[PDB]
Amino acid sequence: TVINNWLLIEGHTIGIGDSIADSKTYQDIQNTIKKAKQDVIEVIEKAH
Amino acid sequence: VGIRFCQECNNMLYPKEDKENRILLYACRNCDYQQEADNSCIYVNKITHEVDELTQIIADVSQDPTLPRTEDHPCQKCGHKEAVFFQSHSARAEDAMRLYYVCTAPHCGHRWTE
Ligand SMILES: [Zn+2]
Ligand SMILES: [Zn+2]
C-alpha cells in the first residue's frame, strides 16, 4: 500500500527513448559486428 | 574387377579352381562355358574410402546458377578465370570441407580440388 501510494508521485514508464542508445555506442556495435563477421570469414577461408 | 557375363547365355560368370591343375577359371553354372581368369583378384574392399570424388562429379554442374563461382583459381589446361566451387559429398572420410572446382566455360570440361 505505502509504496504504491508513493509511486503515485514519481511514476514509472517505458518508451522509445529508453531503447535508443548513443551514436558512439551504435558505432562501437557496428564495428564489433564487422570484426566478428570478418573473423568468421577468415575461419571459413581457413577451412576451405 | 567387377562382373563379367557368359557369352552363351548372358549370365554371371563366377570363379572355380581347376582341382587337378591349380589354375583359377570362371565358369557360368547355367552352362559348360569357361574362362581361365585374367583377374588374379576376385574380391577387393576399399574399407577406408580415401578416394577423391573427381570421377563422381561431372562437367554439367558448371551450368548451375545457384552455385558460387570465383575468378581466383584458374583452370590448368585453358586458364579461364571463372570456376564454380562446391563442397564434397562423401559421407565417410577423414575430411569434410575441401572444395571441388569445375571450369565454367561451355567447351572446357576440367576439374580440380583444394
Ligand atoms: Zn553361361
Ligand atoms: Zn578450363
Image (tube, coloured by chain):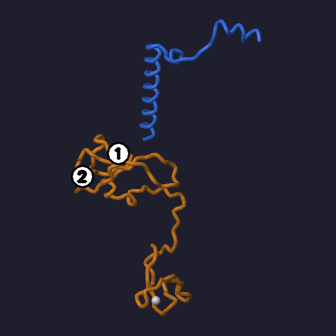
Q: Earlier in the sequence, mark 2 or mark 1?
A: 1
Q: Residues within 10 Å of mark 2 (few under 14, many from 20)?
A: some
Is ligand 2 less than 8 Å from the beta carbon at label 2? Answer: yes
Q: Nearer the viewer, residue B94 or A3?
A: A3
Residue at horizontal 46 percent and vertical 85 percent from the top? B11
> Marks 2/1: CA distance?
15 Å
Q: Residue B24: x, y in percent?
A: 50, 82
Please tell me whether mark 2 sits on a helix, a strand or a loop: loop
Q: Residue B112: x, y in percent?
A: 34, 51
Q: Nearer the viewer, residue B35 or B70?
A: B70
Quarter of the rendering containing residue B56:
bottom left
Chain A on-screen colour: blue
Q: Nearer the viewer, residue A23 or B47?
A: A23
Residue B33 image label: none
Q: Residue furthest bottom?
A: B32
Chain B on-screen colour: orange
Residue B68 image label: 1
Residue at horizontal 76 percent and vertical 9 percent from the top? A2
- The answer to whether residue B68 is left or right of residue B42 is left
Q: Tag 1: residue type? A: Pro
Q: Residue furthest right?
A: A1
In the rendered image of this protein, does residue B67 appear above or below residue B20? above
